[PDB]
Image: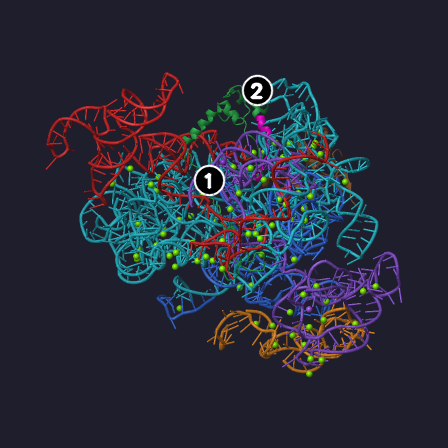
Chain colours: A brown, B green, C blue, D orange, E purple, F red, G cyan
Amino acid sequence: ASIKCGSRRKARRAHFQAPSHVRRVLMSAPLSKELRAKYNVRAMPVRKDDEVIVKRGTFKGREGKVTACYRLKWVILIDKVNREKANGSTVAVGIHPSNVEITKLKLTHHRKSILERKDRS
Amino acid sequence: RLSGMNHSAHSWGTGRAVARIPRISGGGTSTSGAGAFGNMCRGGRMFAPTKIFRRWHRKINLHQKRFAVVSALAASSVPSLVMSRGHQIGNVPEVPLVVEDSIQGYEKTKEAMAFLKAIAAIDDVNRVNDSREIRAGRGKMRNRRYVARRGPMLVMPNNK
RNA sequence: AACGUGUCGCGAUGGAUGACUUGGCUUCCUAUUUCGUUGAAGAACGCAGUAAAGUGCGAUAAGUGGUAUCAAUUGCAGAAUCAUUCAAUUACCGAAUCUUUGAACGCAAACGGCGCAUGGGAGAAGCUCGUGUCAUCCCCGUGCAUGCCAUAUUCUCAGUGUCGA
RNA sequence: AGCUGUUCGACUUGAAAAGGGGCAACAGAGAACCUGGGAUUAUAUUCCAAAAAGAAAUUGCAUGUGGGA
RNA sequence: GAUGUGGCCUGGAGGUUAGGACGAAGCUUAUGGCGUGAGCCUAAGAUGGACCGGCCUCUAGUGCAGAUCUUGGUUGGCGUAGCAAAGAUCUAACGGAGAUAUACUCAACAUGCAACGUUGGAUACUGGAGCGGGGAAGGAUUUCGUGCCAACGGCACUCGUA
RNA sequence: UGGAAAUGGGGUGCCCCCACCCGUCUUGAAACACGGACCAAGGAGUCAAACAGACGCGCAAGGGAGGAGAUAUGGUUGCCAGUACUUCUCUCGUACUGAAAGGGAGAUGCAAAAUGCAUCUGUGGUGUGCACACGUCAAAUCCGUUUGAUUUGCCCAACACC
RNA sequence: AGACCUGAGUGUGGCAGGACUACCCGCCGAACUUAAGCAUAUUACUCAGCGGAGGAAAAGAAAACAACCGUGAUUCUCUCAGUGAGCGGCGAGCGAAGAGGGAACGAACUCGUUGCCGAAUCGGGUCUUACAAGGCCUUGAGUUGUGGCACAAAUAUCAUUGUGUGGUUGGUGCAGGAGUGGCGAAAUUCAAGCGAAAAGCAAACCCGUUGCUGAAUACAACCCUUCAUGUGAGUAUUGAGCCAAAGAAGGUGUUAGCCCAUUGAGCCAUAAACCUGAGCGCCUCAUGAAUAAGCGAGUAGCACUGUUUGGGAAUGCAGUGUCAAGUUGGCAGGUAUUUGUCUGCCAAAGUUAAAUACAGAGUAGGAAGACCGAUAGCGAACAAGUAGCGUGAGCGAAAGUUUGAAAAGCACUUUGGAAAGAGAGUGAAAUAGAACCUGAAGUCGUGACAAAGACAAUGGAAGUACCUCCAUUUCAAC
Ligand SMILES: [K+]
Ligand SMILES: [K+]
Ligand SMILES: [K+]
Ligand SMILES: [Mg+2]
Ligand SMILES: [Mg+2]
Ligand SMILES: [Mg+2]
Ligand SMILES: [Mg+2]
Ligand SMILES: [Mg+2]
Ligand SMILES: [Mg+2]
Ligand SMILES: [Mg+2]
Ligand SMILES: [Mg+2]
Ligand SMILES: [Mg+2]
Ligand SMILES: [Mg+2]
Ligand SMILES: [Mg+2]
Ligand SMILES: [Mg+2]
Ligand SMILES: [Mg+2]
Ligand SMILES: [Mg+2]
Ligand SMILES: [Mg+2]
Ligand SMILES: [Mg+2]
Ligand SMILES: [Mg+2]
Ligand SMILES: [Mg+2]
Ligand SMILES: [Mg+2]
Ligand SMILES: [Mg+2]
Ligand SMILES: [Mg+2]
Ligand SMILES: [Mg+2]
Ligand SMILES: [Mg+2]
Ligand SMILES: [Mg+2]
Ligand SMILES: [Mg+2]
Ligand SMILES: [Mg+2]
Ligand SMILES: [Mg+2]
Ligand SMILES: [Mg+2]
Ligand SMILES: [Mg+2]
Ligand SMILES: [Mg+2]
Ligand SMILES: [Mg+2]
Ligand SMILES: [Mg+2]
Ligand SMILES: [Mg+2]
Ligand SMILES: [Mg+2]
Ligand SMILES: [Mg+2]
Ligand SMILES: [Mg+2]
Ligand SMILES: [Mg+2]
Ligand SMILES: [Mg+2]
Ligand SMILES: [Mg+2]
Ligand SMILES: [Mg+2]
Ligand SMILES: [Mg+2]
Ligand SMILES: [Mg+2]
Ligand SMILES: [Mg+2]
Ligand SMILES: [Mg+2]
Ligand SMILES: [Mg+2]
Ligand SMILES: [Mg+2]
Ligand SMILES: [Mg+2]
Ligand SMILES: [Mg+2]
Ligand SMILES: [Mg+2]
Ligand SMILES: [Mg+2]
Ligand SMILES: [Mg+2]
Ligand SMILES: [Mg+2]
Ligand SMILES: [Mg+2]
Ligand SMILES: [Mg+2]
Ligand SMILES: [Mg+2]
Ligand SMILES: [Mg+2]
Ligand SMILES: [Mg+2]
Ligand SMILES: [Mg+2]
Ligand SMILES: [Mg+2]
Ligand SMILES: [Mg+2]
Ligand SMILES: [Mg+2]
Ligand SMILES: [Mg+2]
Ligand SMILES: [Mg+2]
Ligand SMILES: [Mg+2]
Ligand SMILES: [Mg+2]
Ligand SMILES: [Mg+2]
Ligand SMILES: [Mg+2]
Ligand SMILES: [Mg+2]
Ligand SMILES: [Mg+2]
Ligand SMILES: [Mg+2]
Ligand SMILES: [Mg+2]
Ligand SMILES: [Mg+2]
Ligand SMILES: [Mg+2]
Ligand SMILES: [Mg+2]
Ligand SMILES: [Mg+2]
Ligand SMILES: [Mg+2]
Ligand SMILES: [Mg+2]
Ligand SMILES: [Mg+2]
Ligand SMILES: [Mg+2]
Ligand SMILES: [Mg+2]
Ligand SMILES: [Mg+2]
Ligand SMILES: [Mg+2]
Ligand SMILES: [Mg+2]
Ligand code: NA
Ligand code: NA
Ligand code: NA
């Protein structure tokens, strides 16, 4: 199957050497219960300008807008999720997408096509 | 077949105050003059390298194979032997446990799971579920990550 | 006394051990699966805004085109749009590009050298009315190894070969 | 200005020329430049610009003049 | 030398039964207990941070003190042998963090030593078959300026073919 | 009921007694015989085939493949390269001898036919020989017996003569 | 003059050369070694060397086995068989074949020759939508012979006419599928918050959808106060649910069916090729059915030599010499010869799929493992055939970047020329501070203590002095 298979070595290699477009599907987050009922879709790949809330980790319960999907460090950047450096400047903190939940969807013509074909009804 | 022997690696002789072992030729490298070809040398060939024409498989007499299956079946009808093997059969109605043919009509796992509770086979199933864990040792690095107990065996008349 | 000895607590030097494993080794299977003068394999130079190596690519040079896919890449920077597309990025592939070489084959070679044909190009001298044209010089393309096969709107020849006029 | 004949260069009949194509010398053979500079942080018989600091020597094409054809 | 051992130990497999973030493996020990022993187990870590124990069976690259054994590291010798051909340096000033660097006492010596580069003087050497000025082979940026002193120039450097 | 009283264990020193350096070759090593500075990790009877004996297991005058096929499986990423099923075959034995041509093994009875007849519940015979069955003695008995020896019959497995 | 024979030049259109080489085909070809020496033998018709192909190659349609009630191209497998074959200083050793059970198999075809024809043939122009298996033209080639028909799976063939076949004649264009590519499934981030109940006990099962409840008033180094500081992230536990034709093994800050990705029906798009009443139309072109003769010549044999073979008075082959038969001929029938009977087959020309190999190959993908786990496993887990070495042929490493969940990678103060130190901060943890997890042994420094002559030190056995973060026992007439 895709990535996961009978070989742990092959499955892990397929994950950590994934191309950019494969990484997008791996960096997906669940939709909120409001969005799940509206679109009949369990989860969507996170993109920029999405609104998410952290559900797992130290920043659990923090809401903000996705400012970057790094896809090389396997994290997303949220505007309200940050911390202070030694010198006093603010730097963003990366969060794995599977630890957050999408509350608002950035809707494009391409994004509607994905939601339409992923509709379970 | 070539592992540990991919060198020129001639011995130096007795005149030089070193052990008489083949040594890697050349110079300009940390491996030059190093011991070679020996099972006791770093980077050398293992003692008695393993071969693929080892006897992996076995012949068993056809009658002896049927004797074993017959003995295993007779043991499965003894409740004390089943308990001694580790199965939780303390609530099943009868041993051997025979059930009606209608289970082959089930289509949903929900129906099959309800049947296992009726004949009290779910206790042995639950024993397997609680025993699932990561395998201890190197085998988890291979494709043997999870281990569990056996549980009940359901025998059907055919492949349906 | 001092050196020195022994034990314990704590440090240093030194990188074993355990856990970890995108690597190796071994076995098995599936195919409209087998390179090159239509210039291969190999070798050499070069190419990024920033770029030594490596990777990818060839003066269209970390890539052009086309299909999908749908918002990145990312050290920094830059970037029309925030994206049906025409410019994100990945994946794949039909269209292209593909420097010097190398069987290397115009002749050579510790020479980025020197030819013969035939097409071009640039030409501030000269002639012509800054425009034309252009000698010498210079630049670029194509052909030009040897052997063999076939062939010639039935091409040009040689022989005190055999004839026939 | 034409005609005949004629000299010499360009375009289209065939004397005589035996012995294929190339490499091998940065000390042999060959080879038209040499002074001055205030011209550099580092190159120079290699750079210097109209008073070339300047003075030459040599090839390849041409034009005009002089003289032959 | 033979044989036996519900004899010990190690990496994996089929079973079974357990443990671990209230801390797995590994490691440490004047931590004791058990066993004739191989070893097993507990305690503590002011260690560690994620796996793993017992028992039955199966299996194998399964147990080290020495092979002038292999590889890595360490080590007494030892601040020891030495760093002695090519004669040689001295002085002031400038530069430099490299100084004239100080509890008390205390005028300076007896409490910051020794070492650098440049320039000017002094002294000396090479002595034209030269530590002179140019080339071939070989090397290929060592050339030049500025900056710099972690490593390197077996002493040193503020200097350098670093 | 305590920074405790005991006993055991552990650590260090001391006293009196003992006490040649390990591994190796060798008749003989503490040797003026060789290998031996320290530690870590690595390091050497293995896999395959033929035969034999012991032991385990199945079947037995028969045992067993192998190759292959069939279908549960024409299925499933995988489990499933396993398991289940089959063979007028092949092989090792039930028979051995001879260089070969070629022959090829029961007993009893009756009898002596250069292929003799009859019968088929039968160790070819003899000696020594477990158990068992008839007794017969001895000792001891809790008086039920046991525990030794021996006679006779049959003698199993074996051994020895034929 | 010219021809045609032989041989040249040039133009036009093409092909060869090199790479790869695991397996395969042809040649060439050792020795170490074994024989307890060694020469025949063996290693071995092997390594090295030189050539040549392909997805396989080679072999292949009987001049074959057999001796039977007969089998029937080739290849491969079990077996025949380590052989009562055979070869062999008959030593060491070596060593097959037929039959039988199977795999595969639509498996068969072409030329030469002989008869009967005879340029009906081939190229090259040109036209038909066409370098047509077509028409027309063509001296160009070919009569020193290209093609046609018939030769045991056979028994006429050649015109006619109707019957109807070829999707492998060539044009033209029309479907479905397979194959590829993309897309495409469920269910808790549910409830309980923190050093100590986000823990347990009611001892098969049930009771239990219930009852019961804290020996952590914790611990932080001689102990006694007092004052501070300390618990990262819930894939853990407990309780309550849910999905499963999906429990499948990857990811995510601890161990996840329900956080993410996967795991299925199905949908969409397609150069050619492939499969489908030899898929289905049209034009064109092809095409089926209702008397004698021969059969492969420096070849086969034979002789000598050499080699190879289990092949032994010679199993194949090579060189030279010599060299047939075809008037019941020839070859084989595993002891040489000469006879005569029998059996099988018909050499000296060619093509051919599968079953088989891939023993150091490649392309595009996949599936795995009782394997190794950074001195192991490929030399290479990493800018590895790299750095480096050698004139060269060649030789050839060491190296896990494994900090942390996240860089949050130590601002700022102070001493120092700097390197750094001392503080202060981040972080659950800097003794996690950048070749940064764990951090052993050996060696060394330091503080404390034990002592100790010179008996080298270590060791054994018994005591003793002092210590002991060790264990166990006892603490009332016990
Ligand atoms: K014992
Ligand atoms: K060493
Ligand atoms: K041979
Ligand atoms: Mg889903
Ligand atoms: Mg190795
Ligand atoms: Mg568990
Ligand atoms: Mg382990
Ligand atoms: Mg090229
Ligand atoms: Mg050339
Ligand atoms: Mg050439
Ligand atoms: Mg003539
Ligand atoms: Mg020359
Ligand atoms: Mg020279
Ligand atoms: Mg000269
Ligand atoms: Mg010159
Ligand atoms: Mg100079
Ligand atoms: Mg192992
Ligand atoms: Mg276990
Ligand atoms: Mg201690
Ligand atoms: Mg100790
Ligand atoms: Mg154990
Ligand atoms: Mg070993
Ligand atoms: Mg060791
Ligand atoms: Mg040694
Ligand atoms: Mg020292
Ligand atoms: Mg000294
Ligand atoms: Mg000296
Ligand atoms: Mg001197
Ligand atoms: Mg001076
Ligand atoms: Mg002073
Ligand atoms: Mg001073
Ligand atoms: Mg002098
Ligand atoms: Mg002198
Ligand atoms: Mg002089
Ligand atoms: Mg000189
Ligand atoms: Mg310099
Ligand atoms: Mg120095
Ligand atoms: Mg004594
Ligand atoms: Mg000796
Ligand atoms: Mg002696
Ligand atoms: Mg000794
Ligand atoms: Mg002596
Ligand atoms: Mg000796
Ligand atoms: Mg079988
Ligand atoms: Mg017998
Ligand atoms: Mg016989
Ligand atoms: Mg050998
Ligand atoms: Mg020998
Ligand atoms: Mg010998
Ligand atoms: Mg010898
Ligand atoms: Mg070879
Ligand atoms: Mg094939
Ligand atoms: Mg072939
Ligand atoms: Mg046959
Ligand atoms: Mg046999
Ligand atoms: Mg042989
Ligand atoms: Mg057969
Ligand atoms: Mg066969
Ligand atoms: Mg035509
Ligand atoms: Mg013919
Ligand atoms: Mg959560
Ligand atoms: Mg919750
Ligand atoms: Mg908790
Ligand atoms: Mg927590
Ligand atoms: Mg998650
Ligand atoms: Mg998981
Ligand atoms: Mg699917
Ligand atoms: Mg049809
Ligand atoms: Mg013939
Ligand atoms: Mg002949
Ligand atoms: Mg031979
Ligand atoms: Mg012979
Ligand atoms: Mg011969
Ligand atoms: Mg052939
Ligand atoms: Mg498997
Ligand atoms: Mg290492
Ligand atoms: Mg390695
Ligand atoms: Mg290595
Ligand atoms: Mg803090
Ligand atoms: Mg630590
Ligand atoms: Mg740490
Ligand atoms: Mg560390
Ligand atoms: Mg240490
Ligand atoms: Mg100490
Ligand atoms: Mg002593
Ligand atoms: Mg004592
Ligand atoms: Na000195
Ligand atoms: Na057609
Ligand atoms: Na199609």
The label shown at residue A30 is none
C11 up-or-down from G175: above or below: below
State the quadrant of the C terminus of chain A.
top right
- What residue is rendered at 44% in x and 29% in y? B68
Q: Position of residue B139 (x, y in %)?
A: 56, 38
Callout 1: few (<14), some (14-19), or many (20+) C-alpha neighbours within 10 Å?
few
Callout 2: few (<14), some (14-19), or many (20+) C-alpha neighbours within 10 Å?
few
Viewer-side residue, B19 vs E106 = E106
Q: Is residue A37 visible?
A: no
- The quarter of the rendering in which ligand 65 is drawn is top right
Q: Which element carries disc 2, helix, strand or loop?
A: helix
Would you say the residues marked 2 and 1 are in contact, meaning their CB atoms lie under 8 Å apart? no
Left/right placement of residue G80 relative to residue E65 reads left
Subunit of mark 1? B
Q: Amino acid at mark 1?
A: Trp
In the image, the segment drawn in magenta is: B125-139
Viewer-side residue, B132 vs G7 = B132
Q: Position of residue B22 (x, y in %)?
A: 51, 56
The label shown at residue B56 is 1
Left/right placement of residue F9 relative to residue F115 reads right
Viewer-side residue, F157 vs G377 = F157
Q: Which element carries disc 1, helix, strand or loop?
A: loop
**Dot 2 beta carbon under 8 Å from ligand 6:** no
Q: Position of residue C141 (x, y in %)?
A: 61, 59
State the quadrant of the N terminus of chain A.
top right
Q: Is residue B49 visible?
A: yes
Q: Which residue is mark 2?
A: B118
Residue G199: quadrant of the picture: top right
B40 up-or-down from G158: above or below: below
Viewer-side residue, B142 vs G325 = B142
